[PDB]
Length: 126
Ligand SMILES: Cc1cnc(Nc2ccc(C(=O)NC3CCNCC3)c(F)c2)nc1Nc1cc(NS(=O)(=O)C(C)(C)C)cc(C(=O)N[C@@H](CCC(=O)O)C(=O)O)c1
Image (cartoon, rainbow, N blue to C red):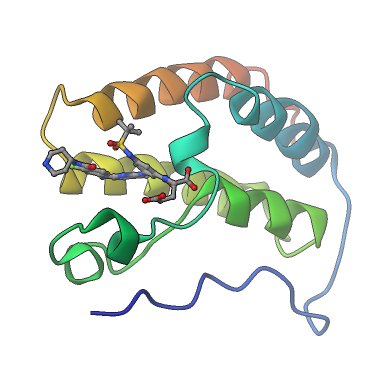
């Protein structure tokens, strides 16, 4: 089947606030993962058509990627920091659902998740 449209990243009707937690999520957490050797397979939605991935968007009905997260942070899409943390965790979980344990993409996701947890350990208080 065709790829779905990407997740929404901006909504002018959503209320906007800046918090220490959201700032840290963009400037520390996202930034660190984005520059990692293994960021690139996660920097945009999975193009399952081009990659010929069987049934990808039947298996993965809550897709998420770091390009979407980055835009959401930049557009003040998130009100609560937990919304952003949940999006990262959805991305990791989705990788572990679709792909065999120990395969290359899974090892890349695990390396990014380890870094994510290191940085989240120092998230500012609410
Ligand atoms: C986030 C994510 C999750 N799950 C997957 N599952 C995949 C993906 C690919 C394959 C694959 O190619 N299997 C071969 C053919 C069938 N038999 C076995 C060998 C696979 F089996 C599973 N992939 C995700 N992300 C992702 C992965 C990859 N490649 S990869 O092999 O996993 C690796 C080199 C190890 C990272 C590429 C991109 C990507 O975005 N590439 C281009 C645009 C697309 C294009 O040009 O075709 C870009 O960078 O823009 C993204």
